[PDB]
Image (cartoon, rainbow over all chains, first blue to last red; front, side, top):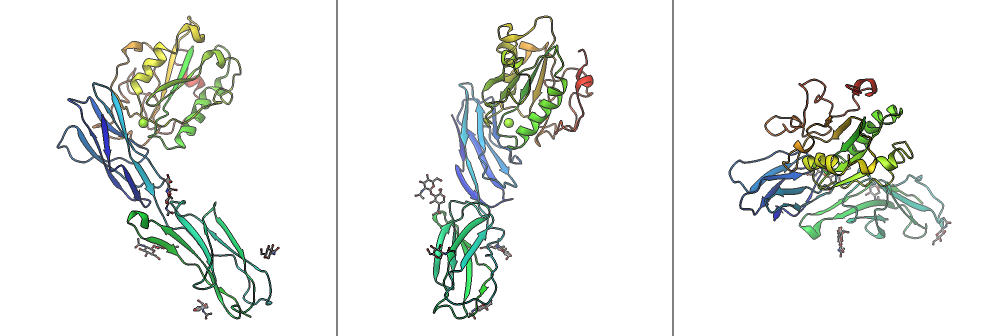
Amino acid sequence: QTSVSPSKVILPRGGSVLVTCSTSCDQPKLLGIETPLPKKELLLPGNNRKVYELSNVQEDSQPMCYSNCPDGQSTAKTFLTVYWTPERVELAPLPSWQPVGKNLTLRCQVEGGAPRANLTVVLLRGEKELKREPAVGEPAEVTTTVLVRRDHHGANFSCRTELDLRPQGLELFENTSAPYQLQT
Amino acid sequence: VDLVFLFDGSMSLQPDEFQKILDFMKDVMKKCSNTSYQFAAVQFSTSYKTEFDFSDYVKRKDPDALLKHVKHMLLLTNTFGAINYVATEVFREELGARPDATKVLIIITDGEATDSGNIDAAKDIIRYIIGIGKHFQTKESQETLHKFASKPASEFVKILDTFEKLKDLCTELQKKI
Ligand SMILES: *[C@@H]1O[C@H](CO)[C@@H](O[C@@H]2O[C@H](CO)[C@@H](O)[C@H](O)[C@H]2NC(C)=O)[C@H](O)[C@H]1NC(C)=O
Ligand SMILES: *[C@@H]1O[C@H](CO)[C@@H](O[C@@H]2O[C@H](CO)[C@@H](O)[C@H](O)[C@H]2NC(C)=O)[C@H](O)[C@H]1NC(C)=O
Ligand SMILES: *[C@@H]1O[C@H](CO)[C@@H](O)[C@H](O)[C@H]1NC(C)=O
Ligand SMILES: *[C@@H]1O[C@H](CO)[C@@H](O)[C@H](O)[C@H]1NC(C)=O
Ligand SMILES: [Mg+2]
């Protein structure tokens, strides 16, 4: 007959959260939370309701509120989601000058970033989308063979990341990378 | 001596601490693979299961052949009901225990109970609880590490939140072996 809130949460590393292990029993013999995270309990007022503070959470943890009620021990599970902007989004160095009409390769790698099912990567020669693909692995390998013709005369190529937490009230967390000074 | 390892497979232990625990089990077990030395293993969380019984134990003696299908459950931590499992459904002669032998109990847990039980059902067994977490700090909350204690505050409950901070417990764990 347990219960807990909030049921879902999204937060950055090292962040802290509060959780209320509630319960509905005539007189429960025990109430607590089950987590690998550092616990710190709150107020004394109340009996069948308990609040804590899960601190310094770095991995997507999932606390578990329990309760030994006369009827029995039940469980209420919450879900902690950690999100963060990658270490480096920079792309692989090629030299400034290049022979036109060259099927040269543009490679970009991103290391980190979560939640990984929301983080996309995009290679681009200026404000033109060259290729948008989801971050795969560590670092995230991504490549698109660019040509040297007409829009190629002394351009600047770059690599950005877009982490969409907008579907859950946050913002779009993106990071641009050091430019590619292409000349010809 | 029919010794038993009772390790904590609850969520509250870092996914690593599970494997750091096993290392210790082996620090005593395989190091003391000498004959006339029987062991067992019961991972406790919200539920219980005998990881490896005596029967399959003395068949392929090695802590890398008995942990074939170990799966980290990571639920609660029924510490009491765990001890009361080693008693009733573990030390039963049926499985593979020798009568004229001392029944030891090696409990491994951060010392955080998710229930309040009673171990009088096996108060005679040689207890041996080893901390490992972070929770094992203040007396106001953490005190149950004293509940399963036997003899005076000696080498029963120390700072060893990493039992790795200890050499080979062969000639050391033989307190009556
Ligand atoms: C962020 O991650 C989730 C998880 O992949 C994206 O999609 C949903 O994921 C849940 C599981 O977490 C699935 O059960 C749903 O089927 C998914 N819903 C969808 C995508 O329709 C979520 O959309 C991601 N946000 C973005 C847009 O990247
Ligand atoms: C990636 O982008 C994020 C935001 O989109 C950056 O976060 C901010 O970083 C600056 C330093 O450049 C800090 O001063 C801000 O305080 C951060 N945001 C906040 C919490 O206000 C992040 O730094 C970028 N990553 C890199 C590698 O610099
Ligand atoms: C040049 O680009 C084409 C475009 O699809 C690709 O098929 C080809 O393999 C590339 N050349 C290389 C690097 O072999
Ligand atoms: C080219 O790269 C430089 C270096 O950051 C940048 O300042 C400039 O705006 C870019 N555009 C061009 C092609 O001049
Ligand atoms: Mg636990």
